[PDB]
Length: 197
Ligand SMILES: [Fe+3]
Image (tube, rainbow, N blue to C red; front, side, top):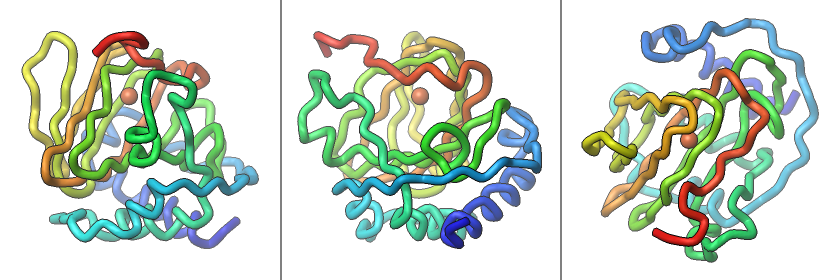
């Protein structure tokens, strides 16, 4: 429906295809049932739209498209009643494209955008889905329990085994990423340390 979302999908489908780490993770079913989205705006959206420093190589289209459908997105508010403050809540940017709260439905995958501004810590978090982080724009640090950290640029990617604690920290750069889920799509991410860290 909303042509913002229309263009987005199409930018999704084509990158998926061009990118082995995506196409290797999940097959695109081709073949997604449309569903209405109730818009929710949050300040992070503003942030994403505004950020002058979401730099790329090969991934401007999708990026722009992510931005464009931002106006119509269901912005999420995961971590709501946690230990995380508005500091977090008003900076951490996420919406659904494929799945719950997104314009398209699927039993096989979900797809998302993550934005984070500079000077932010995304604390250690976890979920049942298997995960891929494909970076579109800027750069950030990726954290994963028991592995050395990785600085992630564009077209870089990280795999998250099930339940595996992972974190992100931005320094002076922002980033945007495509995030794909497979497996248990229904269980929302939770903080690994709801009281600490
Ligand atoms: Fe995750």
